[PDB]
Amino acid sequence: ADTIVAVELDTYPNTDIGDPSYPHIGIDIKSVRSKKTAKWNMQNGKVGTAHIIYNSVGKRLSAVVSYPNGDSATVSYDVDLDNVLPEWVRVGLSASTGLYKETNTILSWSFTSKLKSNSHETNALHFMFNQFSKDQKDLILQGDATTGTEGNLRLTRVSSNGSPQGSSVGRALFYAPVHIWESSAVVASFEATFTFLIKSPDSHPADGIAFFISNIDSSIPSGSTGRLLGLFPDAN
Amino acid sequence: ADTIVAVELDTYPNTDIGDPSYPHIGIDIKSVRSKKTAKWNMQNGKVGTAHIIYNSVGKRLSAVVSYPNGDSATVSYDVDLDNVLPEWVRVGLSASTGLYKETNTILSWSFTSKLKSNSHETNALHFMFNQFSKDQKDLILQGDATTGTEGNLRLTRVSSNGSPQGSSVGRALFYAPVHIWESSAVVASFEATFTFLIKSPDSHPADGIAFFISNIDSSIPSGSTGRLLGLFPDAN
Amino acid sequence: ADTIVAVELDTYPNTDIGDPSYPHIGIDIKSVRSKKTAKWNMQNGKVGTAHIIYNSVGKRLSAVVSYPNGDSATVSYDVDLDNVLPEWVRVGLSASTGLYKETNTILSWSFTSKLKSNSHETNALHFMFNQFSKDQKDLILQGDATTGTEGNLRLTRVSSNGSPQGSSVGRALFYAPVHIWESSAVVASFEATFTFLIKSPDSHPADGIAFFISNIDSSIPSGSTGRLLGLFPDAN
Amino acid sequence: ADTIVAVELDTYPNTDIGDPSYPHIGIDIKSVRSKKTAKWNMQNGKVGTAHIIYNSVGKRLSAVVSYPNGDSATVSYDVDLDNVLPEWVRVGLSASTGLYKETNTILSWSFTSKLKSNSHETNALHFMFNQFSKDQKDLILQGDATTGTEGNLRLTRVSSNGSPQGSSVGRALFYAPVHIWESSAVVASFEATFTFLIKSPDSHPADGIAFFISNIDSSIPSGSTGRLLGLFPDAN
Ligand SMILES: Nc1ncnc2[nH]cnc12
Ligand SMILES: Nc1ncnc2[nH]cnc12
Ligand SMILES: Nc1ncnc2[nH]cnc12
Ligand SMILES: Nc1ncnc2[nH]cnc12
Ligand SMILES: [Ca+2]
Ligand SMILES: [Ca+2]
Ligand SMILES: [Ca+2]
Ligand SMILES: [Ca+2]
Ligand SMILES: [Mn+2]
Ligand SMILES: [Mn+2]
Ligand SMILES: [Mn+2]
Ligand SMILES: [Mn+2]
């Protein structure tokens, strides 16, 4: 059912479904098998930042994930998202654990969409969360996601003693639909930034965090924990 | 039930409920009887712009409505909106006709809310509509409001032949709730701008347009057409 | 001397120096011979909008020029501007006439540069001119450029009777240097938008308008009127 | 000569020139004797944030200074800055030490000015420094001010061993002039935010930090160290 465009921060190589044999960032267009990936060194317990950038002019969905020591991974993929997404969408963040686990803590998330037509006629949506609240009424939380008093978005279950749990899936979508393209726009652009804290005591962290764009009514697909990152009903 | 803070562009003097005896802009806090007004020369058939500005520092809700020839009216009112509004709100635009009538056409609407805490931790919501679409999924339309193909928001009924109808009420609220204050914010500010086209063939235009802030579940009060501008169940 | 990156709106095909045999938009990196062009139908006397977009992630300089009837031309070019430009620059607008002529009237110009590092540490510059004033102290006007009372930037000479003159060159650069890249930035992006009105009574319009980025001390090169668009000392 | 509007973070009570007998924030219009002040508990060695807000609608210059534990001081003052400032200005930050001393370290500074006319015609300037660089070409440094490799703006002299020096004055002004009012603007607003770190080993910290607005050619007045905060030739 859902149509998904996602940038995944994939901490666990599932080499039997396309993953390269390392942690990676990837651009996912309607499939968990990334159309493009790049090797990503996830820094356990460090606060990372992902930036996702698209414009309809260059038609390049780009993402960069960095940590404070400056190591970064970038992935870009040429794609015309007008042909992929419906005109109205919701944007959100998703994360998973499976057999292995990790905290999928989002510390901030910002997003901007703009449709520039002809002629000083722009429609724009911008939000920025640097602090999430307990009762975050402009966010739709799905599955295991929760917003804490500590001001974070915990996309997957973390135990009272601070421990990430396995087989968790959770997503947070901005409440308002976004008009991410409009056929008379000369420029439809968006950008998204989030900061995250992936920490694991496990033998390996898993499974990752994705920023995604979906149909407005998108919900977690059945059994999308683990390697499917809460975005896809399957690994096709 | 609803809690309303509004800036009204009031085209019709209802002198028996507080209006001054002229068209006016006013600041309405939980009552249609404006706490403060200023004489406003509505320019029939011209495109006006209203700007509404509040910050929690100066605690002054300010509004200015202007037309291209530069005539403008300003109203300011000292008020602590933390004590008025709930923490989460919806923001919107409302307009009415009663016995007299006018087009209450909104050509653009923009809004920004920011909560600045301590410490480069800001939450922000910004939207901008310069063109409304027919199926405007990030707007909640109430009552007679409609968004047209022409890219406008018609808050009240306009006849197929372009004529405004009487006894109309309509509102458009942004879909996402807004967090307009948060007690640990050092600055909670917002601003709103809209452009409007009030045209009437009537002996007098009525009744006006308001930008308002309300509880998230706000709906048009019963019999709020006319002088109550779709905001208030009564003239108290 | 100068280093120039430019998006040109080139109204005159100078086929002996690389131009294609039509009006075109092009991306110029250190040469007037565009690395990339696209056919552009200049609409005489209509107000056009150009949008220029770059990010250091996708490393794609993109431009689109459109008119209100929606005809548009787009050009994109993969390039790493960190390797082209100095770290600090000035940004501006340039236009020329030669043997043929045209008004090169800019009605608005906006620009944003951002350097996003690690870690909610962004440097940003944004300006927007929708109205230029006579004494525009945040603009550096070179050559024939002038800002009028009418609120426009006339990059090339227009006669008192409204007529564009030949052999004119003029540029307007934003006063403050811009830091358009910084090697520790994870994202260095910029965007620029301007609206323009190219009108000509001539047998052909010429020569065009460019948005450019240059070294801070950039000045009009000698004999850069006409086909060199006020950017290049020569056609190499 | 200079015309100064300033918000001062005044760490040292100079009770013989108007200061109240405590550290205070104040709004200074053409005089170091603040038109309005508020008691401010400066938290030695903590990172503070000041927010300064003005709009020409409400005509209230407002400032709030806060620290992460949430203690804050606010000051507001009704004033029409169109009658005070010239139309074009420079904006900057100033700080002083005298007999007592303190670090006057600025960690970030952001500013926005907007002139909204009639009719989707806004001029705007926004800058944001979250990191200052050594060679900060869009800043004018005066007196003792320096930008470090550490990414801070040290408005006053700090010794190689980290110690603030006495009798220091330094200012940083944004390079481009700002058009802070224009008589046909319906709204002329600005806001400024900076974060600062005032640390002192002294028996008392002194003298403070100001954000100011001045004539474009403003320079440090002779003998404006200490209680005059680098803004005023005297205490009148
Ligand atoms: N370790 C793994 N490699 C490939 N595909 C998988 N699916 C689940 N676990 C996997
Ligand atoms: N003309 C009017 N004056 C005062 N109050 C009113 N209520 C309805 N019409 C009115
Ligand atoms: N018409 C033209 N074609 C090619 N190059 C030129 N240089 C000057 N005019 C020219
Ligand atoms: N301590 C102080 N009190 C008042 N004015 C002053 N000027 C210099 N030092 C002072
Ligand atoms: Ca995986
Ligand atoms: Ca009324
Ligand atoms: Ca040419
Ligand atoms: Ca003092
Ligand atoms: Mn993957
Ligand atoms: Mn009224
Ligand atoms: Mn060319
Ligand atoms: Mn003082």
Image (tube, coloured by chain):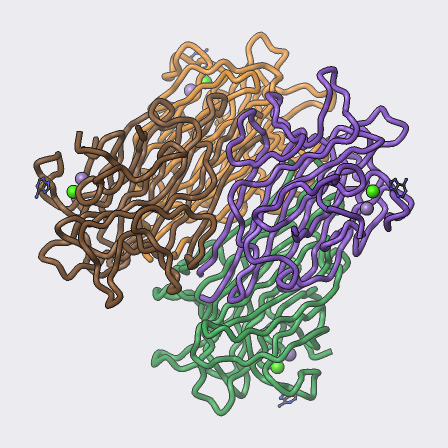
Chain colours: A green, B orange, C purple, D brown
Q: Residue furthest top?
A: B203
Question: Looking at the picture, does residue D66 appear above or below residue D26?
Answer: below
Query: How many circles with numbers are drawn on the protein?
Result: 0
Q: Is A59 placed above or below A199 here?
A: above
Rendered-image quadrant of the N terminus of chain D: top left
**Which of the two residues, B194 or D53, is positioned nearer the viewer here?**
D53
Decide: is A223 above or below D209. below
Q: Say which of D65 and B129 sits in front.
A: D65
Quarter of the image containing the C terminus of chain D? top left
Quarter holding residue D228: top left
Ligand 3 appears in which quadrant?
A: top right
Can residue B90 be seen here? The reply is: no
For the question of whether residue A201 can be seen, the reply is: yes
The answer to which of A195 and A231 lies nearer the viewer is A195
**In the rendering, at what x and y percent does residue A109 appear?**
49, 61
Using the image, determine if residue C183 lies above or below residue D226: below
Q: What is the x, y in percent for residue C122? A: 47, 57
Tell me if B228 is positioned left or right of A120 in this view: left
Q: Position of residue C53 (x, y in %)?
A: 66, 52
Residue D176, x across and y down, in percent: 47, 40
Image position of A194 (left or right of B188): right
Residue B163, picture quadrant? top right
Which residue is farthest bottom? A203
Q: In this view, does D45 lie to the left or right of C166?
A: left
- Residue name at image x 86 percent, y 49 percent: C17
Question: Residue at (60%, 31%) from the top-left corner?
Answer: B144
